[PDB]
Image (cartoon, rainbow over all chains, first blue to last red; front, side):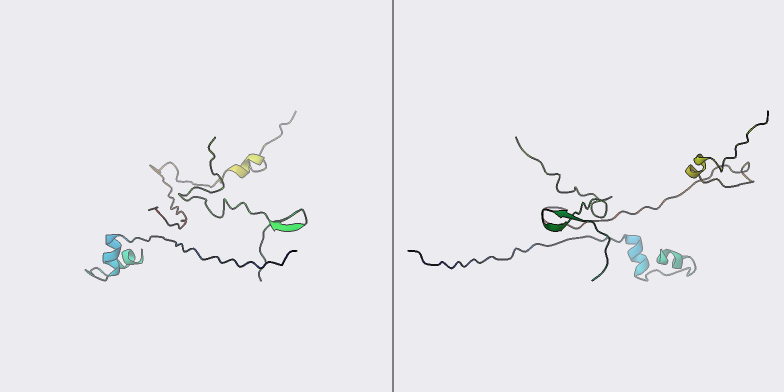
Amino acid sequence: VDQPVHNYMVKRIHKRSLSAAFAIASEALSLLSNTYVDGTEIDSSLRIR
Amino acid sequence: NARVPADLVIVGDKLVFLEALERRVYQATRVAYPLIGNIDI
Amino acid sequence: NTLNFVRFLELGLSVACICTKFPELAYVRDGVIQFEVQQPMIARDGPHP
């Protein structure tokens, strides 16, 4: 004679990640830091670029 | 919900999607597409 | 007999080029074109740079 069975199963999570890089050059960093400002009509275009 | 252009096929008695994402994703990048895996014999 | 005159626009080959009129072509020493093409990026993890 048989009896009915109950099953208990437990799973767990698995952790991963994603990575992406983003670089700015030294000249653009010097333009964005508002250091050595001079000739405001010709450096504004470089800053906008 | 939003309306999206995507094809739907019927297999057996189930309505499934059929995506072949190779132009939307993995195009003009530096990564290799999966589902092109290798076998060893 | 009379000839059947061909115009280039009515031909099917006119779809393969962009014709444009330029009168001062004899003075042009060098003419250039420019392209700025960017590419997408996928994001991953693990033992990858």
